[PDB]
Image (cartoon, rainbow over the protein chains, first blue to last red):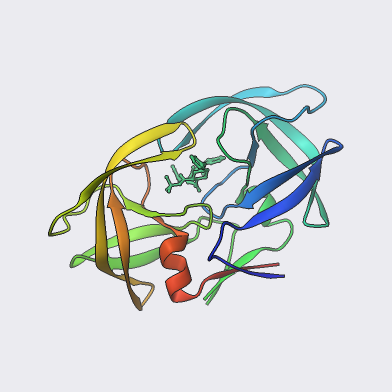
Length: 99
Length: 99
Ligand SMILES: CC(C)(C)NC(=O)[C@@H]1CN(Cc2cccnc2)CCN1C[C@@H](O)C[C@@H](Cc1ccccc1)C(=O)N[C@H]1c2ccccc2C[C@H]1O
């Protein structure tokens, strides 16, 4: 589908058997979620954004359904103010910017 | 044109007679640059992102040529790790997300 930017580009996602809304965020290299229970091991990771750095855990090979599309990739979990889907996943569902 | 997301969606922009590289950021409501000298009055403003909040200057009605398209809008200038073009300006040039 085509999505204009006159509002935040939100999409509903299923991940870990849980439902959530993420913002399609071409400015984010990675994907991060506020609070969701993910199974298995993880590696610490400290990401930098506007306003500072945050400590988060990294989960790889995580199945995630974005707007009805099925993809798998690394998903971060940490103290973010908004759930974001990054280019690491937006590439998998073939998302592009147009103008 | 059409821009895939396998790399950061950077575009060249001219603002205040200066040249800058900016990130097409669908996840950002506003536009902000690290260090540019814009003329006229501004209004203090505090924005929040992942990792924290930062105090910035808010200049309105600022001409900005994005990827060869001329638009005018609110541009923020503050301590950001990367220049970002937000939806407030993306809508002006008619950018959409596609998949
Ligand atoms: C208006 C303003 C510009 C302050 N908005 C944001 O920063 C929003 C904030 N929300 C949240 C919010 C906060 C307060 C109120 N409402 C909403 C979360 C999403 N961001 C947009 C991000 O796309 C910004 C980029 C900026 C950046 C690029 C390169 C280097 C440093 C900073 C960003 O945060 N990028 C990083 C990033 C982000 C997520 C996951 C991984 C990574 C890595 C990296 O690409």
